[PDB]
Length: 48
DNA sequence: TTTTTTTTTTTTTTTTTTTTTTTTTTTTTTTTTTTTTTTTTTTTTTTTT
Image 1 (cartoon, rainbow, N blue to C red):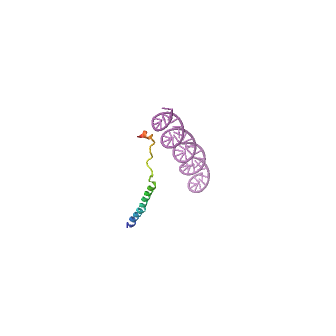
Image 2: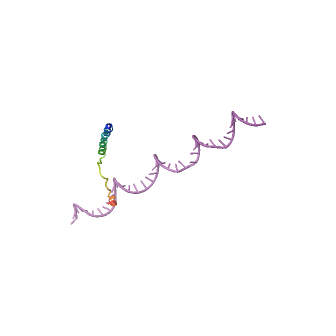
Image 3: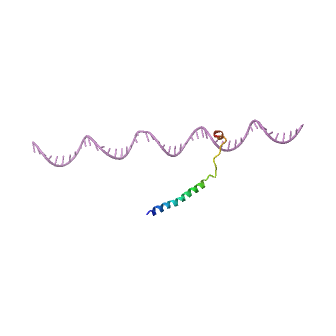
Protein backbone atom coordinates (compact mmCIF):
# COMPACT_ATOMS: atom_id res chain seq x y z
CA UNK A 1 0.00 0.00 0.00
CA UNK A 2 3.04 2.23 -0.51
CA UNK A 3 1.83 3.05 -4.04
CA UNK A 4 0.56 6.45 -2.87
CA UNK A 5 3.71 7.13 -0.86
CA UNK A 6 6.30 6.29 -3.51
CA UNK A 7 4.46 7.69 -6.55
CA UNK A 8 3.94 10.88 -4.53
CA UNK A 9 7.65 11.04 -3.74
CA UNK A 10 8.39 10.65 -7.46
CA UNK A 11 5.87 13.42 -8.12
CA UNK A 12 7.77 15.78 -5.82
CA UNK A 13 10.99 14.66 -7.51
CA UNK A 14 9.49 15.31 -10.95
CA UNK A 15 8.20 18.79 -10.20
CA UNK A 16 11.50 19.48 -8.43
CA UNK A 17 13.94 18.50 -11.16
CA UNK A 18 12.07 21.40 -12.76
CA UNK A 19 13.30 23.53 -9.86
CA UNK A 20 16.83 22.28 -10.53
CA UNK A 21 16.50 23.36 -14.16
CA UNK A 22 15.06 26.67 -12.96
CA UNK A 23 18.17 27.19 -10.83
CA UNK A 24 20.32 26.39 -13.87
CA UNK A 25 18.39 29.04 -15.82
CA UNK A 26 18.93 31.46 -12.92
CA UNK A 27 22.65 30.77 -13.35
CA UNK A 28 22.44 31.34 -17.10
CA UNK A 29 20.86 34.74 -16.46
CA UNK A 30 23.42 35.35 -13.69
CA UNK A 31 26.44 33.97 -15.59
CA UNK A 32 29.01 36.67 -15.31
CA UNK A 33 29.50 38.23 -18.74
CA UNK A 34 32.42 39.77 -16.80
CA UNK A 35 35.61 38.89 -14.93
CA UNK A 36 37.37 39.69 -11.67
CA UNK A 37 37.57 43.47 -11.02
CA UNK A 38 41.09 44.62 -11.90
CA UNK A 39 43.84 46.25 -9.85
CA UNK A 40 44.51 49.98 -9.63
CA UNK A 41 48.35 49.99 -10.00
CA UNK A 42 48.51 51.00 -6.32
CA UNK A 43 47.01 47.83 -4.94
CA UNK A 44 49.82 46.47 -7.11
CA UNK A 45 52.36 48.01 -4.73
CA UNK A 46 50.24 47.04 -1.73
CA UNK A 47 49.54 43.34 -2.34
CA UNK A 48 51.97 42.36 -5.10
C1' DT B 1 73.38 78.97 -41.54
C1' DT B 2 69.04 75.68 -41.25
C1' DT B 3 66.20 71.61 -40.03
C1' DT B 4 64.53 67.26 -37.42
C1' DT B 5 63.72 64.37 -33.36
C1' DT B 6 63.83 63.35 -28.46
C1' DT B 7 64.06 64.37 -23.37
C1' DT B 8 62.73 67.48 -20.20
C1' DT B 9 59.22 71.42 -18.00
C1' DT B 10 53.77 71.80 -17.20
C1' DT B 11 48.88 71.04 -17.75
C1' DT B 12 44.25 68.21 -17.60
C1' DT B 13 41.23 64.42 -16.25
C1' DT B 14 39.75 60.14 -13.58
C1' DT B 15 39.48 56.50 -9.79
C1' DT B 16 40.13 54.89 -5.36
C1' DT B 17 40.39 55.71 -0.69
C1' DT B 18 39.00 57.96 2.99
C1' DT B 19 35.40 62.83 5.61
C1' DT B 20 31.00 64.19 7.21
C1' DT B 21 26.10 64.27 8.06
C1' DT B 22 21.28 62.39 8.47
C1' DT B 23 17.73 58.89 9.14
C1' DT B 24 16.04 54.47 10.63
C1' DT B 25 16.08 51.03 13.80
C1' DT B 26 17.04 49.19 18.41
C1' DT B 27 17.74 49.51 23.54
C1' DT B 28 17.03 51.35 28.58
C1' DT B 29 13.49 53.54 30.76
C1' DT B 30 8.96 55.61 34.91
C1' DT B 31 4.19 57.00 34.61
C1' DT B 32 -0.44 55.26 34.36
C1' DT B 33 -3.51 51.71 34.43
C1' DT B 34 -4.83 47.10 35.73
C1' DT B 35 -4.91 42.76 38.78
C1' DT B 36 -4.93 39.98 43.33
C1' DT B 37 -4.89 39.26 48.51
C1' DT B 38 -7.28 41.19 52.36
C1' DT B 39 -8.91 43.48 57.59
C1' DT B 40 -13.30 45.83 58.63
C1' DT B 41 -18.16 45.89 58.52
C1' DT B 42 -23.10 43.68 58.47
C1' DT B 43 -26.59 39.89 59.20
C1' DT B 44 -28.84 35.81 61.67
C1' DT B 45 -29.49 32.16 65.31
C1' DT B 46 -29.13 29.98 69.73
C1' DT B 47 -29.12 30.18 74.48
C1' DT B 48 -30.10 32.42 78.85
C1' DT B 49 -32.56 35.67 82.03
